[PDB]
Every structure is written in C-alpha cells, then in structure tokens.
Image (cartoon, helix red, strand yellow):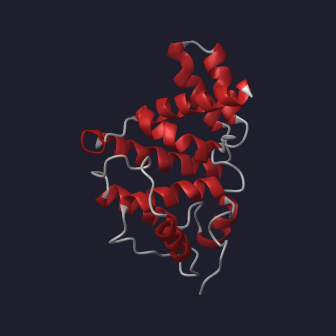
C-alpha cells in the first residue's frame, strides 16, 4: 500500500517508533546495494541519476512494506535518491548549528586539533542522528576505499554530500563560509 511522504520528510525519531531504527530498512538497503554492487561506478554521488527513475525509487520506498529490491537499478539513481532522502529530512542530519560550529572550528581551532574539535561537536548531536551519521560515515568510507575505480576522494564525496547532510542554503559571505567549512569538516570526517 502506497503512503506518499511516509519516508521522505519523516523524522528519525518517528522511524524509530515505527521500525525500531532511525533509518527505514528500505533506506539501509539502498546503501547496501551501492556498497555491494556499485562501488566501481565513476562519480557515484556526483553524476546525476534520471529524475523519473529517482521518483520511481522514492515511490517504492514509500510503500507500506519496508523493503525494496534495488537490483537492476542504476547506481546514480540510487545515490541521488539517497541524497534526496537526507535533503528531505525535516531537520538536517547534522542539525542546523553544526555548519556554524564547523566554521568556528576552522576559524579558531589549530590544524592538528580540528579532528578532535569535530568529534567533540558531533558527540553533541541527538542519539538518532549520531547512529545515522556513524552508519553513513562508514558507508562513505567504503566508497572512498574503492577510489581507484570510482574516483571519489573524501573531498569529492564531501563536496557532493554536504548540502544534503547539512541543509546548506544553496542557490551572504557567512553562508558561503559555512558551506566551505561543512564540506571541509565532512571530508576530514570521511577521511577517517
């Protein structure tokens, strides 16, 4: 049975109410499919998928049964759908404050302490967000492991994923600075 808006736009806490976990299984299966079968696809997360196929995948995800079979799907549609998932969250995965906190980190904290200040900032995120960010970072880390094939460095992933994870105000210098800080901070994070 089809319930539009049952996944995209739903808060992490409600997902836990419904299924036991902050990400729906249908969403976790998208990551598994990318990780299992799509890591040789050049420019994963960067190259655009096809809107109509991205829309069909959203719709399969918003079926009442929390299970989607992704086989046969282009990696780029799945990757883009994943980005839309985080984009449509009612509050960014990172929360709204962290783009600013990452900026302060790059404004004040010294090179060799930044990772440490980034981990400190992250430990302040809600539980759900912390679980999801952990699962995502290990996933993105696997992607970057296959860099010789897909050409996605921590920096290449970061630049493509920050807006959706942080909800950056994308088309003020401070806003652009937050964008750059969030990207840099995210790249650092993926790199470990």
Residue 92 in percent (x, y) is at 67, 48
Q: Kindly indicate the quadrant of the structure image that contains residue 37.
A: bottom left
Return the residue found at the far bottom: 1
**Toward the viewer: 101 or 130?**
101
Residue 72 in percent (x, y) is at 32, 71
Residue 102 makes an appearance in the image: yes
**Residue located at (35% from left, 55% from top):** 35
Give above or below for 61 relative to 40: below
Residue 176 in percent (x, y) is at 66, 29
Q: Is residue 157 left or right of residue 88?
A: left
Q: Kindly indicate the quadrant of the structure image that contains residue 1.
A: bottom right
Give above or below for 114 relative to 162: above
**Residue located at (30% from left, 52% from top):** 41
Q: Is residue 4 left or right of residue 162?
A: right
Return the residue found at the far left: 148
Residue 192 makes an appearance in the image: no
Q: Kindly indicate the quadrant of the structure image that contains residue 175.
A: top right
């Amino acid at each position: 049975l089809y319930f539009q808006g049952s996944v995209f736009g739903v808060p992490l806490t409600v997902n836990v109410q419904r299924t036991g976990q902050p990400l729906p299984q249908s969403i976790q299966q998208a990551m598994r499919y990318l990780r299992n079968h799509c890591l040789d696809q050049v420019g994963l997360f960067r190259k655009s998928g096809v809107k109509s196929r991205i829309q069909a995948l959203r719709q399969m995800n918003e079926g009442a049964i929390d299970c989607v079979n992704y086989e046969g799907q282009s990696a780029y549609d799945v990757a883009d759908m994943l980005k839309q998932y985080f984009r449509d969250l009612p509050e960014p995965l990172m929360t709204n404050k962290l783009s600013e906190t990452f900026l302060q980190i790059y404004q004040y904290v010294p090179k060799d302490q930044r990772l440490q200040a980034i981990k400190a900032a992250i430990m302040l995120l809600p539980d759900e967000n912390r679980e999801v960010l952990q699962t995502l970072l290990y996933f993105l880390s696997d992607v970057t492991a296959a860099v010789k094939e897909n050409q996605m460095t921590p920096t290449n992933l970061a630049v493509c994923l920050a807006p959706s994870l942080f909800h950056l105000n994308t088309l003020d210098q401070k806003d652009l600075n937050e964008n750059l800080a969030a990207t840099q901070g995210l790249a650092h994070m993926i790199a470990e």
